[PDB]
Image (cartoon, coloured by chain):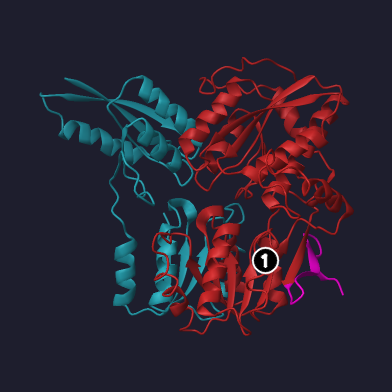
Amino acid sequence: NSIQIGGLFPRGADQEYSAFRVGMVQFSTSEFRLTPHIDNLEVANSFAVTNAFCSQFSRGVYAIFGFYDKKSVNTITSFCGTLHVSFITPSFPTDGTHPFVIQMRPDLKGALLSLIEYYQWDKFAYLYDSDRGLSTLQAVLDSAAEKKWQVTAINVGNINNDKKDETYRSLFQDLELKKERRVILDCE
Amino acid sequence: NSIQIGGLFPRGADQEYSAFRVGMVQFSTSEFRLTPHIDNLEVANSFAVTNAFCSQFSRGVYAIFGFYDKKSVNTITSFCGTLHVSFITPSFPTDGTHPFVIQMRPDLKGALLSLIEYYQWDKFAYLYDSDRGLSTLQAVLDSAAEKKWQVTAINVGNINNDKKDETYRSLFQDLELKKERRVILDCERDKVNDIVDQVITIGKHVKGYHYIIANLGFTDGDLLKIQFGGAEVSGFQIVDYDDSLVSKFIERWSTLEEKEYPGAHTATIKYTSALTYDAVQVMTEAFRNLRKQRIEISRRGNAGDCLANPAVPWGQGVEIERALKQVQVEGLSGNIKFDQNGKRINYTINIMELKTNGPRKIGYWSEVDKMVLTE
């Protein structure tokens, strides 16, 4: 019993793949064996992801395990839905109800909002990164209307890293106008 | 000289296609003719967009004109960048620097922020729609830190329309806790009318309220309703109907048969449609500057499958890009110019206010001069 599956690992996912290998060993049985076809591509590039998907699809796989970015996520959810191919991913949950997609990562949106109320926060800074989608950003902003919060959302993502210092100094300069002492870091 | 191009029109883009046709006629020359291959697909569906692109690519096109959504935008920008295919679109500008993409829509982010300071706003509500990306939302939020604003951002997009009433009542209920009287509507021409209608129903359109329509089509929507209410309404207009150029266009547009040209028998035109017309002119001047420059780029309908691996970009595409981006003519949307990326530059966006006698230009916005009032 040989079950062929696809593996889309972004270049740099060393520990992720290492854990993927250990899993293959710990959950290997005589009843059937899984045959992973690994494809290391730039997960961000939508085009490349399309090829890696169609390639693993032509090879005739039964399921695909990989990752997606805020840019390529739509490609996966769409193709997997049209071709009825199952896609298991540890990446951030999809913003909606996309069939044929298995998400390993639980929704943190709920746990975050609950924690804020626990500490009884009414005014806080929210430094976010657009990498995992503004799904959680919308969450705190929408709740800021109901729970009446004064959130200071700041995209700390588009900061160019080859000179990112006069930006941080100018970042906490705005976080001092209101003397912000409570910050939420929504980043990788 | 037959130049084949692709056309990706979302189902429902009647006036956009009608304007696309009129452009084909107004900019048709004997030197060369453009052969549009139209494909009507659900722009939102990323999969469908992928097929429509590879289909037009196998047919061997030199350039592609179409639209994209907040979901399919990444597909276009990616493929067009890999296959070196040029993509002209009136849709919202891409959030970054994506090569091989020509954007007809100027960035409103700048004009909006300038208008806010003009009215000297410090606390306002920002009703946004996630359809055109949160690019402008991040803009006002980031500026809210520097300029010190108390912005109340509310996603008015995910509102289910088959019961969307107990939601609006609960929407202006939160906009009453802080007695919000200044609202910014960042939505499409449709979602705006829905809000405007609700506003009139609850009576929040009387003197004391101030609305700002965050789009390039201020006169594109119905304003006669919130015109006599009392509340001041401002917005942005990209299609100046005071230009003899645009005025002449309407003279022929308003007369066209509505049967053959759907939604084309009016005195006005949606900014999306106006950009489509200007898009044709850009593609014409581009392919013309290649003939006069003695540059051979011609090929056949055998580019092959787009999924070809390894994917080899045809060098003739690099020149087609340097052509479109080098174009500089005068259109309905003012002076048209581009940078190395594709984002429009040296443009003008008129700031509009709604008075008793109707809309009225109170000034303009230049990327280099910011806001400038016309007395």
**In the rendered image of this protein, which colour is used for chain B?**
red
Chain coloured cyan here: A
Residue at point 56%, 30% (across, down):
B53
Inspect this view and state whether residue A113 appears.
Answer: yes
Q: Which residues are magenta?
A: B354-375
Q: Position of residue A27 (x, y in %)?
A: 15, 33
Question: Residue type at mark 1?
Answer: Leu
Magenta stretch encompasses residue B359:
yes
Residue B58 quadrant: top right
**In front of the other: B300 or A72:** B300
Furthest toward the left, the residue is A30
Residue B81 quadrant: top right
Inspect this view and state whether residue B188 appears.
Answer: no
Q: Is residue B318 above or below residue B244?
A: above
Q: Where is the N terminus of chain B found, in terms of image quarters? A: top right
Q: Where is the C terminus of chain B found, in terms of image quarters? A: bottom right
**In front of the other: B50 or A185:** B50
Q: Is residue A161 left or right of residue B25?
A: left
